[PDB]
């Protein structure tokens, strides 16, 4: 037992990380088959980042201007193209460490592991949620651009995120692996508004079920509620409205613990209205929203990958 | 910027994980060079776990009784020996994925990454501290025994922990890779007392410095204190006494932020005496003690591994 914020094992992704240098700019790229993916702003200088004309900047570049290094291995670039906010560098060698993989666009409230990298070298791994406002709260220093987010299902790596930016507010933005930003963000040095964010209600309830499975049960009460009454509380506390789709996804955890989803909603309502009263739940003094119901079932079941 | 509880990239360790089966018991082993390391209680049945005579149980076993599988690869066992609480299975093939590595015994209050594994297959990675009472608060289901803890310095993996037990209180115990338990624990199914635990003061102060570097500064105050006065507060709140050795280790962070260590101690004293007043620090509503000063400098500096 016990419950921790756990990331996927990073090995299959470590094998794909490279360094991409264009002129004086260095960041990370992802080497899959004979293609290297990286943020398009590798072609910019600090001067350019105000309002870059990426089409004009890339026209100045030839294949031999993109230096790609995997550890000591130098890769030969034989093609380049821009897709949305990413550059695709065709190389003459397929990555021998390419895992089974897909590209996916994740939904807000879904979770993924980030492999933070600098100069193509893995630094660390942590678990993130895509916020309702399409930002992530990561850990990314200058040079982390091109680090990727992913999930693993058995042997298949689903890449969902590439790091592009830190907003002046200190939060993080990036793209899917086709180079489309999550949220309204653009790859330029401007102040950019993120939506007002909300708490991911279905994830808090998943985590409450994780707490009960692990013997933290002090917050269970004598009460129940309705979807309608609960959503009035959710509104007041800036929580996502709970839908029957969310109730359905919580079905397995409700079945395991024997606690009806609306009974767990009545526990959450009391926690929102009264606070934690100086107590903790699974080592936390606030309501945690970065575990999906699938996360909770996986960690409670001991699912593995190859 | 941003600050997350980040684990080491797990790839070098994933390459070393195997399954070890003896009779009907299956758990994880660590394949380094031509030796597989695993918990000795692989040789027990549930019946045996009350008070196992491990010397007598191992005498009944021959090399061919230990089934070792790395993915599909079956390994040939050519020797076995018990060292303290671990079994060392000599195999006829050196692991080709063996990283540069050392075995280390970590000190209480130090941190490490855990690769949780089941049937020799990696499940997830998370960051842990060795508690002052030599327990860890992990996430370990039945079959996780033999999962390992580690740190990485550049290309060298320092193995510090192998998982052996969950205490009836739901906390976790294990050994170094020479098979010596951390703390007073024994590998048998008995109730076993853990020491009274304390909060790792030097780690809380490290994390306060991380908070200031990341722009969380609401807890900084007009006050200072002395080591003596601070330790009176530490006692009352079950924090480790702070020593000059701890002040010295905090020197780099004090230098970066320009906040004297005893000034940061006066912030911590006010936080212990007044609480957080419904506010957060780096996303936490309590005082976090699982980042070492070295952790904070690494994450703030972007150190990488190969
Ligand atoms: C990120 O884009 C990244 O890692 N880019 C490459 C250049 C490392 C990162 C996050 C915004 N950007 C920067 O770190 C960069 C600072 S730097 O050029 O000094 C890199 C340092 C390791 C040497 N900031 C530029 C930037 C802003 C916005 C953006 F979307 C991309 C880059 C800056 F400051 F010019 F605007
Ligand atoms: C752990 O020792 C482990 O993973 N061991 C091997 C057997 C998987 C783990 C934590 C205590 N122990 C158990 O999971 C085990 C339950 S089980 O045999 O049903 C394993 C299950 C996946 C099939 N508990 C035994 C045990 C207690 C204490 C100990 F130190 C080791 C084992 C028990 F219950 F018999 F005591």
Image: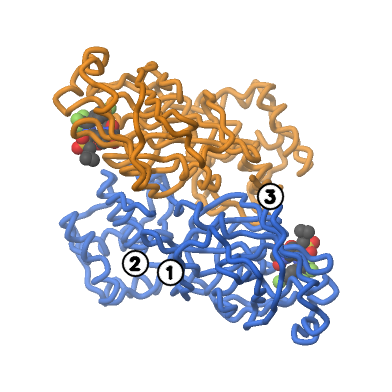
Chain colours: A orange, B blue
* Circles 2 and 1: CB atoms closer than 8 Å: yes
Q: CA distance from mark 1 to mark 3?
A: 27 Å
Cβ of mark 1 under 8 A from ligand 2? no
What residue is rendered at 32% in x and 36% in y? A68
Q: In this orientation, which residue lies closer to the viewer: A47 or A139?
A: A47
Residue on which the image places disc 3: A302
Q: CA distance from mark 2 to mark 3?
A: 34 Å
* Residue A21 position (above or below residue B257): above
Residue on which the image places disc 1: B109
**Quarter in which the N terminus of chain B is drawn:** top left
What residue is rendered at 52% in x and 62% in y? B98
Q: Nearer the viewer, mark 2 or mark 1?
A: 1
Q: CA distance from mark 2 to mark 1?
A: 9 Å
Image quadrant where residue B152 sits: bottom left
Q: Which residue sits furthest right?
A: B47
Residue A51 picture location, percent across and down: 20, 17
Cβ of mark 3 under 8 A from ligand 2? no
Q: Is residue A273 visible?
A: no
Residue A220 picture location, percent across and down: 68, 45
Q: Which chain does tag 2 point to? A: B
Residue on which the image places disc 2: B202
């Amino acid at each position: 037992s016990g419950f921790r914020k756990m990331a996927f094992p990073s090995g299959k992704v470590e094998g794909c990380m490279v360094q991409v240098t264009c002129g004086t700019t260095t960041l990370n790229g992802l080497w899959l088959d004979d293609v290297v993916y990286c943020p398009r702003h590798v072609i910019c200088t600090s001067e350019d980042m105000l309002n870059p004309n990426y089409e004009d900047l890339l026209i100045r570049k030839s294949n031999h201007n993109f230096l790609v290094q995997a550890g000591n291995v130098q890769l030969r670039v034989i093609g380049h193209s821009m897709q949305n906010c990413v550059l695709k560098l065709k190389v003459d060698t397929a990555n021998p460490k390419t895992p089974k993989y897909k590209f996916v666009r994740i939904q807000p409230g879904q979770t993924f592991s980030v492999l933070a990298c600098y100069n193509g070298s893995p630094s660390g791994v942590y678990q993130c949620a895509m916020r309702p406002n399409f930002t992530i709260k990561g850990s990314f220093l200058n040079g982390s651009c091109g680090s990727v987010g992913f999930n693993i299902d058995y042997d298949c790596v689903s890449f969902c995120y590439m790091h592009h930016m830190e907003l002046p507010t200190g939060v993080h933005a990036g793209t899917d692996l086709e180079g489309n930003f999550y949220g309204p963000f653009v790859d330029r040095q401007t102040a950019q508004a993120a939506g007002t964010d909300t708490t991911i209600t279905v994830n808090v309830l998943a985590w409450l079920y994780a707490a009960v499975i692990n013997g933290d049960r002090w917050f269970l009460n004598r009460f129940t509620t309705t979807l309608n009454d609960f959503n009035l509380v959710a509104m007041k506390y800036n929580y996502e409205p709970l839908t029957q789709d969310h109730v359905d996804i919580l079905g397995p955890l409700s079945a395991q613990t024997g606690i009806a989803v609306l009974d767990m909603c009545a526990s959450l309502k009391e926690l929102l209205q009264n606070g934690m009263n100086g107590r903790t739940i699974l080592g936390s003094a606030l309501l945690e929203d970065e575990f999906t119901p699938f996360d909770v079932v996986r960690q409670c079941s001991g699912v593995t990958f190859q």
